[PDB]
Length: 236
Length: 236
Length: 5
Length: 5
Ligand SMILES: *CC(=O)N1CCC2(CC1)CCN(C(=O)[C@]1(Nc3ccc(Cl)cc3)C[C@@H](C)O[C@@H](C)C1)CC2
Ligand SMILES: *CC(=O)N1CCC2(CC1)CCN(C(=O)[C@]1(Nc3ccc(Cl)cc3)C[C@@H](C)O[C@@H](C)C1)CC2
Ligand SMILES: [Mg+2]
Ligand SMILES: [Mg+2]
Ligand SMILES: [Mg+2]
Ligand SMILES: [Mg+2]
Ligand SMILES: [Mg+2]
Ligand SMILES: [Mg+2]
Image (cartoon, chains in turn orange, cyan, blue, purple):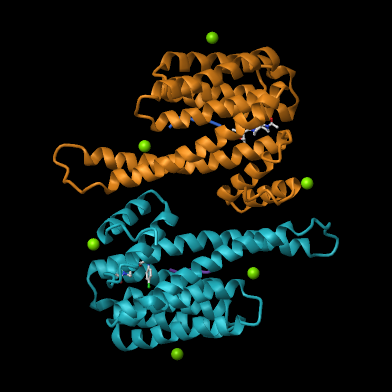
């Protein structure tokens, strides 16, 4: 790997510089190199890994949606034939997106998840696994679509089971997992009722636990709770 | 070249899709492939080429400035020693930026400029040549800095001479060239008086020629004139 | 699109 | 920074 000769601490330092410079592809490559050193990641390091790939794949998803919409319009009645170029370029972007998702899943499987024993690490990585299978599901149209969807579901479910046992209802990781699993239900699994129920119950249980928190923890939890409320407002 | 097997028209089509998707690296690679077909570029095609590389190098320049500022702060008294990483990563971004500039200059030299005979094409390409030497000058700190600056100046000057002979004072290409050459004087050549004089005279001569224009041409010219005014306001 | 983190 | 096009 191209980062094999760079110190772990230097890779982390440069990931933070890349973040400041909004160079998310570089940030992701540095964090991949850091993971491949083989040591477990601290809380801050897990967050850097997640931020980097979330931003890279987020940009790819936005581009894919623009191209997919143009392609859909091209296949409407009365639309002039323009050749294979729109499909080809949508496929190019799609293949790159799938590559990034496969890279992240590969890091999780080799060997982040198997070494993660604390709830905060294990839930966080399993949430990521669910997220990157969800992004694969967004673009899937073939024979493996059901298995891809099920892989997302299974990862989210394991994360949920641990989070409910081991974390308070206001824990930001538990909240963010629930937010994203609810979106999975709505957008991927054709289960809007499940999405709504999950968001509502998560919000309400968090509300009831806010009284236990410091000012700073309260701010952290309420920020994510607002996103649950925003989605509920969108969906009702 | 990786685009050697793709039709010229397909490369142009995909450049336009990439623009819609805000995929400027892809847009630039498609336009490079189109240039390398060896045919001259139409007005619209020249604009696509320029937009693509302007956006790619613009992002690199923004990142370079963030990193250079951090590096400058690191070399202040009382700043803790943090090792070679900031310099290394600034150098990485710098080298990539220089590579993109060299790529654009290479397309201009092989063989866009030598085949450009009409004022609108030749002035546009010479302006681009000035711009990419200016971006090289922004990061230059060594023995060739003076020659890099002079290469920018020479390209802008040839463009100016043609534009004044062959184009009306409201022509958007003449205006954009003058805007950028004025910035060259202010930021690169340590000549703020020349920058101010050029912006003022360009603005005033354009003002006097607006009466000749259609509504649509008026809108085009006045949009760029406002940028001249904005810079004058910044500088006075 | 809905919010995710 | 100043405006360029
Ligand atoms: C060390 C650790 O476990 N972390 C770092 C802090 C963080 C959880 C992972 C919690 C605070 N935080 C956030 O609230 C935001 N991002 C995420 C939340 C939850 C999850 Cl599972 C993933 C990401 C970032 C913040 C700026 O905006 C809010 C809305 C979400 C960062 C991650
Ligand atoms: C065919 C040709 O010669 N072109 C396409 C149109 C254009 C000149 C090059 C003029 C209109 N235009 C602009 O005004 C903007 N960009 C540039 C202007 C001038 C130059 Cl030399 C380069 C670029 C884009 C517009 C959205 O915003 C204004 C402020 C500048 C595009 C290029
Ligand atoms: Mg070491
Ligand atoms: Mg495909
Ligand atoms: Mg339930
Ligand atoms: Mg051909
Ligand atoms: Mg250098
Ligand atoms: Mg003069």
